[PDB]
Amino acid sequence: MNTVPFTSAPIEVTIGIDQYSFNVKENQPFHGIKDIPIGHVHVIHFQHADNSSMRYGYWFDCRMGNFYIQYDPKDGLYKMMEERDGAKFENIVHNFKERQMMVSYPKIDEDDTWYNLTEFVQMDKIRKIVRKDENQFSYVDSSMTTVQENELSDPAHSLNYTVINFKSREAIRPGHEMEDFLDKSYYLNTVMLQGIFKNSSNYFGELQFAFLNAMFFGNYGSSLQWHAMIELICSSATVPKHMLDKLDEILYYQIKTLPEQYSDILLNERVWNICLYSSFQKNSLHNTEKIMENKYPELL
Amino acid sequence: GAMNSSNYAELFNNDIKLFVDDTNVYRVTVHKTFEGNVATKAINGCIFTLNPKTGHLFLKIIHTSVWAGQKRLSQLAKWKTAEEVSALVRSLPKEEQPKQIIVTRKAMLDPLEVHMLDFPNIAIRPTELRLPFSAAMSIDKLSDVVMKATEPQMVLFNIYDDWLDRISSYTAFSRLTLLLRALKTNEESAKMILLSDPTITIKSYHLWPSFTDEQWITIESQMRDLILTEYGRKYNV
View 1 (cartoon, each protein chain N blue to C red):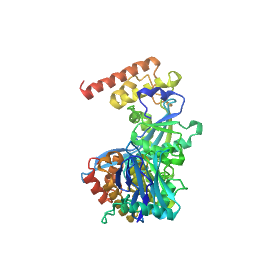
View 2 (view 1 turned 180 degrees about the vertical axis):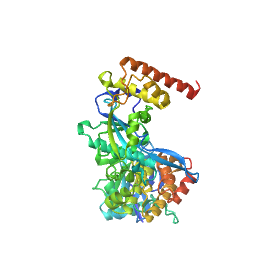
View 3 (view 1 turned 60 degrees about the vertical axis):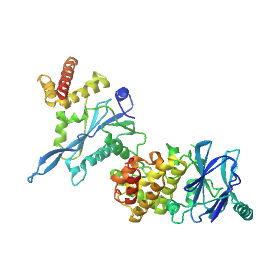
View 4 (view 1 turned 180 degrees about the horizontal axis):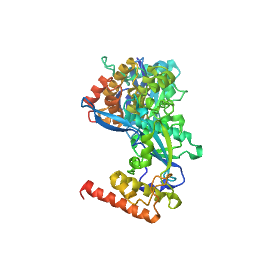
């Protein structure tokens, strides 16, 4: 069980850790989050009480180093940092725990939600989508644009999601125009799975990461990426049976977890209606179709 | 974006552009079977690809053999159209390639865009205009070459005959759309108007009769009258 200590909480802020969140008051004696489950990526995220604009946060894995949060009054945000001195860090964490100034990661034992949302998500893959190689953790916020959004402006602060474009030479073999446009199996299986992602695990990892960025930061480009990766599978007539069964589970937990009130901005009507009712895979996402029909029948 | 009443004059500027109409690509007769079910028999069709500035018509004849053993033909017809237009563009010298292709039907946008990925600088555009190019098969000489085709064939016409010697492209296109609109609304009446005077003939190398400027004014008046009558009837106004 790992710990992310906070030096202090000088400004009033809603702090999220994965799907959980806590209101902290200005100069409240808050010194961090303990009992963080080892074996998963995590995200610690912020929304200032004074600017409900810019949700921002940090993807990390406690196995990769000792991370803490410290408010920077110049840049005006909570920053993640690595403590390289193991003894200084254990000494800081033991003190804060003794004084019970830390919240406990509030995992219910029965609850596999976070595992289910992060099953394929790997810190090494996150660090290639979010490039800042001098840190072991990854900063994401509401406003960061994707490589694809930039093509259609600061590349240092971009989300480098795999570009998916259904009307591209990459997606359409010369001489198979109609076949490849109506059945995207060659784009999914040869270009994307065999070619770029290497396996379905890396593909699902980026799909899950895009969803979580959309949900936790309202990152519009991430939402575009999540939908494109869903639509590429559902629009393929030929998908490995293990991929369809896994996609149904992945989407089920994403829809289950989404705030009921955010369905209007985070869910693309055309993609979902196409995927559940028209696509080749219309009959292959039973759990996802059942949760969508019972939770968001308006959207459909 | 979309071609409409507002940006009409763009059709007659010096940027090469083509209209593509796919209406007559997939043509069928519907009939009863012996068992009293319904079946279709395909007949020869055509792609109507027109330079509205020059009058050059690229009439790609679609022989019924292209449908043999194919499913979902009304869908295939859009992709076959897009394949043939793309092949036409690739066959033209660079300085003759269009800068824009305007499709008369929005269902052609995706098929044409995907076939033209090699030409990212050629803009594929819809139109808000209700163009009567479906009536091309009411032009006797175009109908004759489509129906006689025994194989895929491209036939080149000037749909304006020699009009551009006397009138502007704008005026030539207005006359063409008025003739086709008439032929579309009441073919029998429209064709009666065009041939009633046996002294006015169609040259072997032309599609329409050899009217004087004065006779075109009378003809154009008779076509407008035909169209408004039919409108009152259609609608009871």
